[PDB]
Image (cartoon, rainbow, N blue to C red):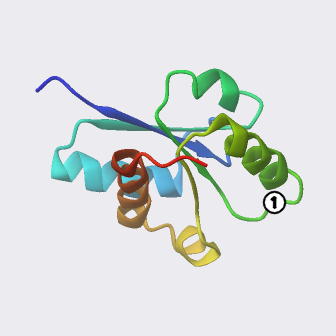
Amino acid sequence: GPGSMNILLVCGAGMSTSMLVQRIEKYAKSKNINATIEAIAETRLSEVVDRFDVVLLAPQSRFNKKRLEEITKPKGIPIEIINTIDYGTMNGEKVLQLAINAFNNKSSV
């Protein structure tokens, strides 16, 4: 029926032409799935999460990951972390797969 999903990515500041976005967009655009993905910072993550469903944080973080996880814990929201390998490799399939997995799983705390 009329349904879809939204995945948020924390790494870039909403720039054009992205590796992860490209791959993921390709797999999805090819599989013909009703889903969307966007990339933004943490500052606008709380404003977008209000509508989004699942959130994903990129590797390499000193305090960013600290606050994020520290906020997600109490917020009780579906947050996934990208492995250094998966990230550096830019595995769109693995990305969208993980996001959807957590979404359906609906886990908290």
- Residue at the (40%, 66%) spot, across then down: 94
Residue 37 image offset from top left, x and y in percent: 44, 39
Q: Nearer the viewer, residue 71 or 58?
A: 71
Is residue 27 depicted above or below 37 in this figure?
below
- Residue at the (49%, 56%) spot, across then down: 20
Is residue 18 depicted above or below 16 in this figure?
below
- Residue at the (58%, 78%) spot, across then down: 85
In this rendering, position of residue 58 left or right of residue 24: right
What amino acid does circle 1 point to?
Ser
Where is residue 71, by image quadrant? top right
Secondary structure beneath label 1: loop
Residue 101 image offset from top left, x and y in percent: 36, 56
Q: Which residue is mark 1?
A: 61
Residue most extreme to the front? 109
Name the quadrant of the N terminus: top left
Q: Nearer the viewer, residue 26 or 48?
A: 48
In this rendering, position of residue 38 left or right of residue 71: left
Residue 57 image offset from top left, x and y in percent: 64, 52
- Residue at the (88%, 60%) spot, across then down: 62
Residue 18 image offset from top left, x and y in percent: 53, 50
Residue most extreme to the right? 63
In this rendering, position of residue 104 left or right of residue 79: left
